[PDB]
Image (cartoon, rainbow, N blue to C red; front, side, top):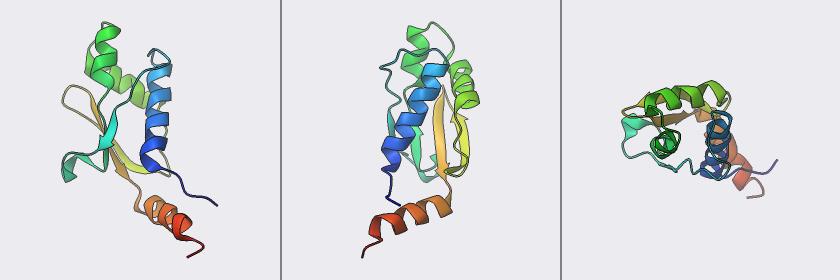
Length: 106
């Protein structure tokens, strides 16, 4: 009944989906708090570097990562923007629960 670190969780999961799509095991998803509210809560910005190393189009890779990424229960919406940014909008019930877990015992 212990809370997660959301950014670290998203990083782990984007990292795995990148690896399933062909990324090196030590690839960096570059998950950061979204730059603007219209880009969700977090963005994964590391697809373009991976795509280049792998010699492929970054939007093509991004779509591949999404086919491996399962954020049901966690994100209400996962969108691809520009040259393969991944924009993640959290489930409000997930956030509220995670925060209730963190403060449980308060």
